[PDB]
Image (tube, grey):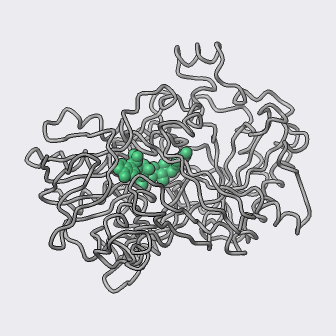
């Protein structure tokens, strides 16, 4: 079946692009998604998101053994349903810092400066909270303050205050380089509001949009230097105008390589026929890494066991109580060196502990390396389109990353030692060992660090002439006509924020690049 545009992947970016491109009734748009409809309860309920790990809603990737982590493999959940990862994520809308775009503008020009992207980002947002927030007030994605924050969360913010991190008046993504805040949420009335909710669903009555679920794309079909369609298991979808890969940091890169687009020698070694030499495909992989500082609680921890009759009754009646929590209720930003300037550390407050020793009754500060120097890549394991690719982030390959995380763990410890928090905790929650000496701390970081689910950069944007660029500033794959990538893969440098915002923004930006308004 024949379309004008074939979009692969109904995720953060792909939902936006399907909705936007189908706004013109004279173009026919296909949105092709490996997963099914987002129908399960645990998709809707903020507190339930982590229960989707290892389910049909999750691709369930893992990294290769990581030398920087002592040989550990790291689990890589990815959403596999309408809305993609926006349907399984932790609902945090934490859109990053204006300076994050300096390396994008360096790579791809003023099209990708902050001034250019800002309206697209603000345009995605509909803030439901108090005035003075930085967020937009008219976009498809409802952004809300928490309905029922844990009582300890105010204490975390007070502790931050005591340690010189003041509360941000606009929320994260404001002018303040340093500070703390309640997490802005992708929630409407206490339930998830995903890209499928905000963008896709309103568009699905359109006669010119076909949403095709349950279909993993195997490769892009190339003919005479142009993408002509995509191959599913049993049939081909044709595109008269463009194929747009929105399959994310894993899937977009894997699909390029499976199509013969990438480094010819490596593709040959994986059993794939090279078609377009583009060595940057799968390279420049970046991700946030976090270490959880977990303490045993001396107070009630509702989020340790949120799914109870009482909480279900309150959620049903009022959409309040623990089930309305995304768990990661507050954030703080700082520099390891204590300077002014853009943050290189984030602290995430979760009033729970992943610790069986205390039955979950603990409190966590996740310490986040926002600007890793480590880099990795994704390659094919072989030519089977159903096989997972080989994911090697190179976590903690750079020793500076270890030192930065060590500094952040010291700061988290400082917070738990603060007047506002120390009364709430009594020792560490195993397997967090609590305070250790300097050398021990470096080893502990390597033993405990894990993904924070923000992988980017495998289909990096850049100007013609930049040998490891994958797409151009208009998101067109270099050396192919009628083929674009629009998702988190194109990001040159991992931001100082959580990447759902960036993916949505790229979706919006891509739609305007492909079909300018007016
Ligand atoms: C568990 C988890 C928690 C997270 N928490 C947050 C958070 O709270 N806040 C935040 O800002 N970010 C968070 N993130 C990250 C954020 O959700 C992602 O970075 C963002 O959604 C990526 O958008 P995307 O469009 O690039 O890809 P995705 O949204 O992953 O979309 C890719 C889509 O393509 C589909 N696909 C892939 N390959 C194929 C194929 N071959 N054929 C067909 N379809 C295919 C996938 O199934 C998926 O639906 C989280 C991520 C995860 C996994």
Residue 480 vs 450, above or below: the answer is below
Give the percent coordinates (x, y) of residue 95: 49, 54
Q: Is residue 504 visible?
A: no
* Front residue of this view, candidates 327 and 152: 327
Give the percent coordinates (x, y) of residue 320: 57, 23
- Decide if residue 99 is on the left or right side of residue 516: right
Tell me which corner region of the image, top left, top right, bottom left or bottom right, holds residue 425.
top right
- Decide if residue 2 is on the left or right side of residue 152: left
* Front residue of this view, candidates 196 and 261: 261
Extreme left residue here?
A: 26
* Front residue of this view, candidates 305 and 57: 57
Residue sitting at 80 percent across and 31 percent down?
359
Q: Is residue 103 visible?
A: yes
* Front residue of this view, candidates 335 and 226: 226
Give the percent coordinates (x, y) of residue 223: 16, 68
Quarter holding the C terminus is bottom left
Residue 345 vs 280, above or below: the answer is above
Tag count: 0
Tell me which corner region of the image, top left, top right, bottom left or bottom right, holds residue 198.
top left
Give the percent coordinates (x, y) of residue 74: 64, 55
- Decide if residue 502 is on the left or right side of residue 215: right
Residue sitting at 73 percent across and 48 percent down?
365
Extreme bottom residue here?
A: 465
Residue sitting at 85 percent across and 43 percent down?
430
Residue 350 vs 413, above or below: the answer is above
- Decide if residue 468 is on the left or right side of residue 482: right
Residue sitting at 35 percent across and 77 percent down?
278
């Amino acid at each position: 079946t024949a379309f004008d545009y074939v979009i692969v992947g109904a995720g953060s970016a792909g939902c936006v692009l399907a909705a936007r491109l189908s706004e013109d009734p004279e173009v026919r748009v296909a949105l092709v998604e490996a997963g099914g409809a987002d129908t399960d309860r645990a998709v809707r309920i903020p507190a339930a998101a982590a229960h989707l790990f290892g389910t049909g809603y999750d691709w369930g990737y893992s990294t290769v053994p990581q030398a920087g982590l002592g040989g550990r493999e790291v689990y890589w959940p990815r959403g596999r349903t309408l809305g993609g990862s926006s349907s399984v994520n932790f609902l945090m809308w934490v859109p990053g810092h204006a300076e994050d775009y300096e390396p994008w503008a360096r790579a791809a020009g003023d099209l990708w400066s902050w001034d250019a992207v800002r309206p697209f980002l603000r345009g995605a947002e509909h803030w439901t909270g108090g005035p003075g927030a930085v967020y937009g007030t008219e976009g498809p994605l409802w952004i809300s303050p928490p309905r029922s924050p844990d009582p300890t969360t105010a204490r975390f913010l007070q502790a931050c205050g005591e340690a010189g991190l003041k509360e941000m008046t606009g929320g994260p993504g404001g002018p303040e380089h340093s500070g703390c805040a309640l997490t802005p949420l992708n929630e409407r009335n206490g339930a998830r509001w995903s890209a499928a909710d905000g963008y896709l669903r309103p568009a699905m009555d359109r006669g010119n949009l076909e949403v095709i679920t349950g279909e993993q794309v195997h490769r892009v079909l190339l003919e005479d230097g142009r993408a002509t369609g995509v191959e599913l298991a049993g049939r081909t979808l044709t595109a008269r105008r463009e194929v747009v890969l929105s399959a994310g940091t894993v899937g977009s890169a894997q699909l390029l390589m499976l199509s013969g687009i990438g480094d010819g020698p490596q593709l040959r070694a994986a059993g794939v026929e090279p078609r377009v030499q583009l060595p940057g495909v799968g390279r420049n992989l970046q991700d946030h890494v976090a270490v959880d500082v977990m303490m045993r609680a001396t107070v009630a921890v509702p989020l340790a066991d949120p799914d109870t009759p009482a909480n279900r009754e309150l959620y049903e009646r009022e959409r309040r109580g623990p089930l309305s929590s995304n768990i990661a209720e507050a954030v703080a930003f700082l520099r390891a060196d204590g300077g002014t300037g853009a943050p290189d550390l984030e602290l995430i407050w979760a009033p729970v502990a992943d610790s069986e020793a205390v039955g979950g009754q603990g409190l966590t500060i996740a310490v986040v390396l926002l600007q890793p120097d480590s880099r990795g890549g994704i390659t094919l394991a072989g030519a089977d389109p159903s096989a997972a690719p080989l994911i090697d982030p190179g976590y903690l390959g750079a020793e500076s990353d270890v030192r930065t995380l060590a500094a952040g763990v010291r700061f988290a410890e400082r917070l738990f030692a603060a007047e506002a928090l120390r009364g709430l905790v009594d020792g560490p929650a195993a397997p967090w060992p609590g305070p250790v000496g300097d050398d021990a701390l470096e080893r502990l970081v390597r033993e405990r660090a894990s993904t924070l689910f923000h992988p980017v950069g495998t289909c990096r944007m850049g100007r013609a002439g930049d040998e490891q660029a994958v797409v151009d500033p208009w998101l067109r794959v270099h050396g192919v006509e009628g083929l674009r990538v629009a998702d988190a893969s194109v990001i040159p440098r991992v931001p100082r924020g959580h990447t759902h915002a960036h993916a949505v923004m790229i979706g919006e930006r891509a739609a305007e690049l492909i079909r300018p308004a007016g």
